[PDB]
Amino acid sequence: DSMLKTKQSYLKLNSVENSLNGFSHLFSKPLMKRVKKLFKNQQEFILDPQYEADYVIPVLPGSHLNVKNPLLELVKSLCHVMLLSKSTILEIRTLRKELLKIFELREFAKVA
Amino acid sequence: MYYGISQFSEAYNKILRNSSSHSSCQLVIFVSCLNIDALCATKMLSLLFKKQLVQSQIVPIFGYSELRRHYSQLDDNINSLLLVGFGGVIDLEAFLEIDPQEYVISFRRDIYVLDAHRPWNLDNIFGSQIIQCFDDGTVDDTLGEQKEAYYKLLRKQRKKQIHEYEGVLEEYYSQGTTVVNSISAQIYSLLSAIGETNLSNLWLNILGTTSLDIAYAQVYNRLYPLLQDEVKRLVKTPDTLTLNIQPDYYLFLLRHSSLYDSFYYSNYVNAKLSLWNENGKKRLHKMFARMGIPLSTAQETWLYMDHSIKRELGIIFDKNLDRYGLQDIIRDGFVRTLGYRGSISASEFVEALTALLEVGNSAQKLTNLRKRWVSNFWLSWDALDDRKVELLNRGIQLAQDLQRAIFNTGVAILEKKLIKHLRIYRLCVLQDGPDLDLYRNPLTLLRLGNWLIECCAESEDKQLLPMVLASIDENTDTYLVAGLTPRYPRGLDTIHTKKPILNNFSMAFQQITAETDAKVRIDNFESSIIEIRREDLSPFLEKLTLSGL
């Protein structure tokens, strides 16, 4: 929805294309707060016995990745889908670094 | 108590009546590995049982799983079994599913548990006849009230007595783990009562007692006069053997390293003078200049060090240490000399033994590490006899190397300020660094923690908080977490020593693991040392923060 809004605004105004440039500015802070809340809740309710139902990793044919923290893969997918822009790469990289700063990880780690 | 101080001999006699045979092995001893006092007691028992030609076997064990498996392996032929260095704090019968009716005939077997930890399982004594221990003089006087409640707990208004008994039992429990007496001291008391004392036994008793100087100085100070009096009661010929009371200092290998390094690596001097930054080195140089020993002279071996200064070192220290406030470094120790070999002190010998234990030579790798540890224990045991000295010079040089490594890691920790000050307990994690593979040894981790807690105590902070230390073993992807008790400054009076500081980390860990399905492995004989998962460390940590310590 944000991408549609920014493209519509750019069109109404008239390897860079200002149709999309500047779309992550709409939801960065709410995303940061939501990621913080998710991390806190996962930290609190991961080793509980009755709350272990929703943290079970699904298994599907062709899967080969053994992973531990589901929130890491959530944010990794949410950032890799963003990283397909090929024109707003710097903004996406800055957002990815800010998200990774919530975890105690670094920018170029293999786990990230 | 089961076996009081005056009954030891009688129990010993029973052993003979059940073990003294011609062609049958009827005695097996299990020893708490990675412990010096247990090693000394085992050596004394081995000499005793080699005197009367009683056949025996010595088996090192590391974890409770090994204890259970080895006991399951044993045959009914073994009449007598010894458990030195552990077993006091847990109920063996529940652990070992012992049926008294299976071993009635009574006294089919006999298991003698000999441990020093003061909080011990009350049911283990007041419930079972098969299991028996040597009390140090605690059940008679301390437990005069708990035994009544246990005996009573072993018309509708009678629930008050049951409630009172339950409350008394709960009050007795929920106590921290401490040590109040020495196994080698108890064994030497038995030897003195029997009449087989000699110089080797006295030396082993001295080693066993002085092994506690780092952590249980109160016990050491309570026990020292007995050793002094016993040594008093008991031409340089190439076969002489001398045990004397010479002044000694809290110094690291004074007679085997240079005096400069001796002052540099000493934990007490480090704590008092802050040698991790440059002002400490400046103060040390001021100290040396004011004493008057040249910097080039102080950096030579103790053998070639100047004879006159070696003679007047006592007066130099007495006149110079007061200004810097190190007048607590001077104490009285034991020195052993044999012929023309040289002089060794008890502190130096125990440091050499500890370092030789440390360094020498998933589940599969853990088993390999544990068998390496038992092999190191056997090599350290072999190093005891007087016929080997290349197994002691190597230990001394390894002690020097290990102390260097510990200092190099601690200075980096104190630079980085990794010690996070929480509301209840301090915390520090060695996430990354050099030579971190050395710290897979719990005894090395305890050495590092002892230095850290001494440094923390020697400060202006007025907070006594437990410290948690953790490491990394990248091959297994597991954290090795050890809980550490706070310590008072060594220069303190006895009025503020009403009770030693207890350790609640074992209770906290067991409660958290019993109420939450964490992936830990609590099997070490030290109940305050656990192995936890890298992903499981944190939630666990918050749990420990939220649980009543």
Image (tube, coloured by chain):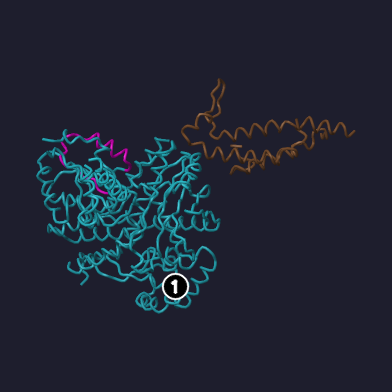
> What is the magenta range?
B62-85
In the figure, the brown chain has which letter?
Answer: A
**Left or right placement of residue B538 versus residue B3 in this view:** right
Left or right relative to B13: residue B309: right
For the view shown, which residue lies furthest in the right direction?
Answer: A14
- Residue B391 vertical position relative to residue B217 in the rendered view, above or below: above
Q: Give the camera-side residue of A9 and B367.
A: A9
Assess disc 1: are there few (<14), some (14-19) or many (≥20) residues with their C-alpha within 10 Å of its C-alpha: some
Q: Position of residue B450 (x, y in %)?
A: 41, 57
List the residue tagged with mark 1. Answer: B297
- Residue B371, image x and y in percent? 34, 41
User: Residue B172 appears at what percent x and percent y?
Assistant: 30, 50
**Which quadrant would residue B350 be assigned to in this image?**
bottom left
Residue B78 on the magenta span: yes
**Per the image, is A52 magenta?**
no
Residue placed furthest toward the top: A61
Percent from the top left, x then y, of residue A13? 88, 34
Amino acid type, label 1: Thr
- Chain B display color: cyan
Q: Is residue A86 above or below residue B469?
A: above
